Amino acid sequence: VNKHDKEALYRYYTGTMEMKNISALHGKNNLRFKFGIKIQVLLPGLDVFFVQEKRDKHDIFYTVGGVIQNNKTSGVVSAPILNISKEKGEDAFVKGYPYYIKKEKITLKELDYKLRKHLIEKYGLYKTISKDGRVKISLKDGSFYNLDLRSKLKFKYMGEVIESKQIKDIEVNL
């Protein structure tokens, strides 16, 4: 029901902070910890992917999903193939290259957010390119995830965790 246009999406997937050293402790399953910034995380279903959704009347910053327990961020490197495809329009291109992930396990939230942010900077998504696009993230077991670019990621998919090794290719269509 809450509609998101190009401007709304662009503003969300730009301005993000990884906290890879937390020990946190609620309504619909939430956690609380300081950073002296008092933070709360909603659990859609310690390393956390922090994206500000809301800041309460007295300085309690809210985010959704992103929390991964016992994760290695240094020493590990997964490079699945990112295949970008804009087939019809003013400038039609195909572009395949490795998408570097320096994390053992990665939340769908971060992969989505960081992947979209990349399409804004380099290809001009939600700026010069249309918001009308899809993304398929294929795993080695043949399973996959679908990101619709027309709307921002539904909160109830941000609690999903992904083994970085298991990702083989990310297919973006514009």
Image (cartoon, rainbow, N blue to C red):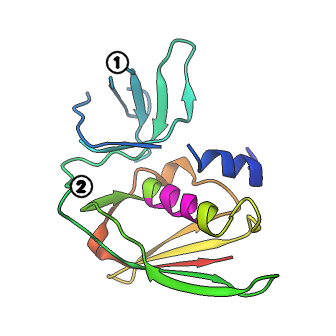
Q: Is residue 5 magenta?
A: no
Residue 70 placement (x, y as % from top left) = 18, 49
Label 1: few (<14), some (14–19) or many (≥20) C-alpha neighbours in 10 Å: few
> What is the magenta range?
111-118
Q: Tell me if 5 is positioned left or right of 139 in this view.
A: right
What secondary structure predominates along the stretch shown in magenta? helix
Q: Is residue 41 above or below residue 139?
A: above
Residue 57 placement (x, y as % from top left) = 57, 13
**Pointers 2 and 1 in contact (CB under 8 A)?**
no
Q: Is residue 122 above or below residue 35?
A: below
Q: Compare residues 132 and 158 and report the one nearer the observer.
A: 132
Name of the residue lying farthest toward the front: 122
Q: Is residue 114 magenta?
A: yes
Residue 166 placement (x, y as % from top left) = 30, 75
Residue depicted at 63% across the width and 72% down the height:
134
| Count of residue discs | 2
Q: Disc 1 on helix, strand or loop?
A: loop
Occupied quadrant, residue 80 = bottom left
Residue depicted at 44% across the width and 61% down the height:
111
Name which residue type carries label 2.
Thr
Q: CA separation, marks 2 and 1?
A: 24 Å
Name of the residue lying farthest toward the top: 58
Q: Is residue 115 above or below residue 4?
A: below
Q: Which residue is mark 1?
A: 36
Q: Which residue is mark 2?
A: 73
Residue 66 placement (x, y as % from top left) = 39, 47
Q: Earlier in the sequence, mark 2 or mark 1?
A: 1
Name which residue type carries label 1.
Gly
Q: Disc 2 on helix, strand or loop?
A: loop
Residue depicted at 41% across the width and 34% down the height:
41
Q: Compare residues 109 and 14 and report the one nearer the observer.
A: 14
The quadrant of the image that shows the C terminus is bottom right
